[PDB]
Image (tube, coloured by chain):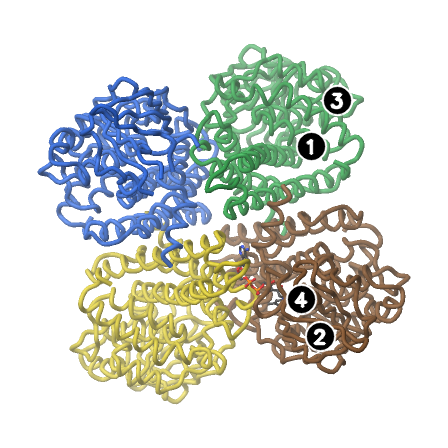
Chain colours: A blue, B green, C brown, D yellow
Amino acid sequence: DDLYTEDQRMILDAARAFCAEVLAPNAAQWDRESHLPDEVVAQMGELGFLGMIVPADWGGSYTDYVAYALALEEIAAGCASCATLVSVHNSVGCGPVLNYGTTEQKERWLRDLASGKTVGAFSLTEPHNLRTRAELRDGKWILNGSKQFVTNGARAGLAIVFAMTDPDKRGLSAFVVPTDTPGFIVGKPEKKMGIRASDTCPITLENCAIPQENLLGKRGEGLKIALSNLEGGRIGIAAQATGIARAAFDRARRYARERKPIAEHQAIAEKLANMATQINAARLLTHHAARLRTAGLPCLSEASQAKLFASEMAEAVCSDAIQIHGGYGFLVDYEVERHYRDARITQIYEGTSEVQRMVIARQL
Amino acid sequence: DDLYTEDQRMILDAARAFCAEVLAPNAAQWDRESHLPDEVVAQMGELGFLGMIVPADWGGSYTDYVAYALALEEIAAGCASCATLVSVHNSVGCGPVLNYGTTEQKERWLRDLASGKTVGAFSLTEPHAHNLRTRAELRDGKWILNGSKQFVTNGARAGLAIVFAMTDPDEGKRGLSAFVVPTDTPGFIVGKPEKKMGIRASDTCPITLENCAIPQENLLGKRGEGLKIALSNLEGGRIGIAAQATGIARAAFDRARRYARERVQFGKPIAEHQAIAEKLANMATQINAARLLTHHAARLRTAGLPCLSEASQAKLFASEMAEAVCSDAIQIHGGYGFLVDYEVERHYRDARITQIYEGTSEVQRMVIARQL
Amino acid sequence: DDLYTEDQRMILDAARAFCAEVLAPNAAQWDRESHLPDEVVAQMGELGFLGMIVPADWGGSYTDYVAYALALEEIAAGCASCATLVSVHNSVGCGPVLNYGTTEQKERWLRDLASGKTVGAFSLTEPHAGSEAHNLRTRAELRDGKWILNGSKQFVTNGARAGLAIVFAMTDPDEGKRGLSAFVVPTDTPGFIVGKPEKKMGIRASDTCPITLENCAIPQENLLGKRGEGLKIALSNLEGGRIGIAAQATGIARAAFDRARRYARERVQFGKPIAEHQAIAEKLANMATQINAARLLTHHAARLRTAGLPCLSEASQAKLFASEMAEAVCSDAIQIHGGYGFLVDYEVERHYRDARITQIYEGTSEVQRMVIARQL
Amino acid sequence: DDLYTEDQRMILDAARAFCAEVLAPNAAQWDRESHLPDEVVAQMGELGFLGMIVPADWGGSYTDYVAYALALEEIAAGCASCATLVSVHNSVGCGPVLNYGTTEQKERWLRDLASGKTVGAFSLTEPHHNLRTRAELRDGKWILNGSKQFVTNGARAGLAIVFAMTDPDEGKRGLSAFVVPTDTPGFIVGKPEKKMGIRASDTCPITLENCAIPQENLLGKRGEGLKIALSNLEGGRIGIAAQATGIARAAFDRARRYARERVQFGKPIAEHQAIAEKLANMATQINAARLLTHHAARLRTAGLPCLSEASQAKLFASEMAEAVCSDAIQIHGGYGFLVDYEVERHYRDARITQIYEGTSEVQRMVIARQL
Ligand SMILES: Cc1cc2c(cc1C)N(C[C@H](O)[C@H](O)[C@H](O)COP(=O)(O)OP(=O)(O)OC[C@H]1O[C@@H](n3cnc4c(N)ncnc43)[C@H](O)[C@@H]1O)c1[nH]c(=O)[nH]c(=O)c1N2
């Protein structure tokens, strides 16, 4: 930990101890029951894990993005579903309100988002850019449409919902929708291969009317807003891939050392060497992008490179962790099978690998 | 199909029909409930799938190994757990009895294995880290077995197990013997099925032998021949798992390519995107190569030629490929690929075991290298 | 071998002897001099390797395509450059004349192509146009009873040694994809100007030449097929071409692997033959497995083609797979050799250099993928 | 660059200018002739490139190891052979004398090594730790006999750090290190080896036949030879990591420019998704390789343990370089296989990085050992 700053090493310690004491012993159960207890979410709130990229005067704990990634790496090593909840809540639950909310808006919502009292959700994508619509009639914005894969959909108190307001690029607007609003209809959580305890829900909007002052930004600023947190999001998920890969690697190398022991059979040792090299490269790409972002510099390509690299790495590293365990690797009680299922999603959400490659290439 | 013989196409069509009518629509449920219905196993019996490498003379359906491979690829595309059952039963349930059994032993057990009335299992490996701790002592005209075995596929539904034990500890490599143990023999204790990431409906159980006393005539082959017997269906087992890996990959590939033709993003079917197209071509290439390696091994095996390397190449290749094709199949589905209801996530989970069992990839590589 | 037919074993035996006696011992020198002696090309002629896909009654030696792939793999295992020459001459030198030639045109040319008295070249690619092979700027105009070719061509294999070239030219510039025509052009024709062979990383003894056509006049009866049929003709030997390159990749890789496995048995490090080191043994096992899959893809495409069945996909899969496999196999061979792997005298560096072209010519990997995907 | 330091940016900018004006225009010709012009070596010396990990007090230009890695990357991108010479000279030419030499020894040789006046070589391995080359103390001199293998800079070096058995029966603690002037009678340098790549980096066998040197040329203590042989592994590996990053980067830069110029089916080929995907993968792996390499250098700069980290950088960069060079070939199509388009030289040069300064297999052993 010698190369990190003092802020960064403090977050790392706090994160480490939380993860060892609360996440790691319970993640198997949470996966098996597809459910993360709310008191664990609340406790993440109290510790500042749900406002790590909100400034401290708005109720958060932001220091820099390297710290953020270190915390999300630790949290993902303990529980990949927690890391999903946290990466989404901080980046796209908190980000839009902080960056485009008026002062009154931030007073209404941001301190509760940043403290974790209110969990946040972001809803842009749709089953088939958009067909969800919002009409302004009699002082209320009225939303009708259908939305897909909303992380934190069941538990969020607020949702940033994107909707077509003016059908002729600047045709979308963003809304803060409290999730108890009549006509905000959240469906049953999707059944997923992995991150099973991170609730991922479809949402139907059926004349969901919200006050006019719940418009977020100016009318027509929807797309820009939806795109304002790609760097933070991708950095977050790259950090998550790194943590999940690292957890499986930690188990593999512990199993190799105990099962001479198999860690000095050439082939096993080569896998472990490869796994360590790849995990460390993923971390360094993640941190490099986080430094640029901390400094306010352009870093979409760098963040997309981290997310790309870390995500693909993680599936291969988790696959080696299984292989190193033999027959036991396929068994639930040995946990690496969980890490393998959890890892897979990182290549898909927050921009697919194909999208990550498009943007990196665009800028060469 | 016009590339295959008459017999082969017939076995292929019979299995296609069974997988479409019975397996494919119910796989998802069986994965969900971690259980294959006894009657579906009995129906594979009735159809000859549980005797495909047993001569017709002994009640089986043997034509050749390519045909075996074709049937297993089809079963696997519909239900990976079914393929596991079928492949283990046929190769290591039926094989030891067929090759090493006396005539009377073949009459007492082989007809029922081949018909599928008796499901067979095979138990050599043990849960500690050749050098077995499980023992057999000859006492008053009976073999008495004491031991603990690990991961017996078909462990719960098998009526017979081939069970290997130390009979002569001084003799080392010739220290082992093989025994046919009816699973209802007192002292044959089946534990709870293991909880696995995939092939969840294939029962995999630890077993203990506790003063498990069996008739002297249940010794399979000669005393001390157990190792040799334990190693004599490696070719067949490995051919079948390579076929299974091929079928699993093919199911996910078929779902993904159909999805890529129907799904529209950026104003064209996604199969018209170059990156997607490249995955689809790589998938088809790798599946075809895996099938070609498998059938080449099968062809050598059918002609009684030595083929342990060719069988191991095919199993190594098909197993590694199946993970990469299934991963690609998930990716082409985007977020839907991660969803249970889109099924490719089941194919991925199921395929991962193929690199491990029937000899790990590491073991496969060792034999292939040994002959180079 | 037991799985092959008597014709297949016969050609296989013949190629093997030739490759040990003539090719393998001299290949290093030819790479070094960037030159294949004419007497070696004549011997391949005499032995029937330049007619392996022309029927016997036209002077060829065609039995089936599996035989062809076996012969090409051997030839390639001894000299990659030689395999390039053979593959091109057979598929696109002979093929166009065989398939589209009149009786008179086959009597004039195909017996000499099939015996190897005359080496064949194929010229389509231009400086601006490779993978997009239809937009041609080379032109052909009828004046005074002769076809007059003017233009510029690129990367012609066998370009300096060939006696005939199948040249593709725009006869009808406003007719697009139906505007190409194919022409048999004697390479001694005035205005058929062969540039100096390209300097390449690998297959350095396979002459690969630019060609300038300048008031290059030929008899009217050197038109091959119907006017406008050029594109169809240019695309009519894809399967055979790709089968042969797949077999070439397989043979180059095999040669690298044979050296590596022998060296790993002999070389000792940390008290045993490095072959017994598990990481080495794994590399060896992966190399065998991949070469074997390549071969089986190639022979499967060869069977469909022998039966006249459609097989462009299967041929493209073999080519893609073999070519990419060969790079990784030759790379493993280098690594198994340690620091000796980088040295010219240890040969495997040459196989690595030679292997790399197989992913590019006879349709790039990207093109192979497009056609495999399209036919799903 | 914003993220580098004033010294880092300083050495980077100088390496850039110099790669661009001297190295990159002439690298093809040097590869073709298998020869680096002496005056170019002298310019590297003069510019401080041959003293980059020796302190300023001893005639060097040492700032930190991140600066070293940046400069090696740039040199490598203009001329892989020059980078091989530079990496070796700094790491194992200067390193032993710097760290194990007496003050008298450092005054005698280290300043000339650091200024580039004298180029240094290092000679441990033989054709077959268990070594045949012997040194015998006789009449106030060490007399060396043996055969040595693949000495980089073997034909231009003025001094060679040679390792020999002083005490055959003490095994690993029976080796000693010696500073040998290369003009010493009985120091016979054979013909440079014929190689696939880095052809202008001279790589020579050396025969020592009754090669007699002063008693005071023992380096470190008698028996300390293996420890000295292993004392610059970190530096060496960081250097080759930077080499591999640079070679790949050169091929990458050519391929990405080509892709924006070459049109096929109506658009620049960089806009075909399959090419874009290659370019994106090349950029990402190259950056990953630099970041591993700089991470290692930071640990080295701070004097912290970093053998594994440098081994990870060297392993990752070297394997990466082959794959990136291969893509660069592919992106060029047929042109990629032609000498005039340069990417085929980069691919050839890149392949050595997986083998020397320890094979991939050796890198992976040290990484594993330490987990
Ligand atoms: C040694 C040797 C020998 C021969 C030949 C080449 C060489 C190097 N060829 C020519 C060969 O067929 C040619 O190199 C390929 O068609 C590739 O074309 P270019 O080199 O013009 O690359 P080109 O400019 O077409 O492509 C550059 C890169 O972009 C990619 N690309 C192009 N279009 C694309 C698309 N739509 N989507 C995705 N990617 C795309 C390609 O795959 C390639 O990777 C030939 N020719 C001949 O007529 N007669 C002969 O005998 C020979 N022999």
- Residue A193 lies in what quarter of the image? top left
- Amino acid type, callout 2: Leu
Q: Nearer the viewer, residue A141 or C232?
A: A141
- Amino acid type, callout 4: Leu
Q: Nearer the viewer, residue A296 or C288?
A: A296
Up the image or down, C332 lies above or below C149; here it is above
Labelled disc at residue C348: none
Q: Whole-Å distance between the Cαs marked 3 and 4?
A: 59 Å
Q: Chain of mark 1?
A: B
Quick check: do tags 1 and 3 share a chain?
yes
Q: Which residue is mark 3?
A: B60
Q: Whole-Å distance between the Cαs marked 1 and 2?
A: 55 Å
Considering the numbered disc 1 on the image, is that residue within a helix, a strand or a loop?
Answer: helix
Q: Residue at x 38, y 49 (%)?
A: A273
Q: Chain of mark 2?
A: C
**Residue B235: x and y, percent?**
66, 37
Q: Chain of mark 4?
A: C
Quick check: which quadrant has ligand 1?
A: bottom right
Labelled disc at residue C149: 2
Q: How many marks are shown on the rendered structure? A: 4
Q: Residue at x 37, y 29 (%)?
A: A149
Q: Which residue is mark 4?
A: C124
- Amino acid type, callout 1: Leu
Labelled disc at residue B70: 1
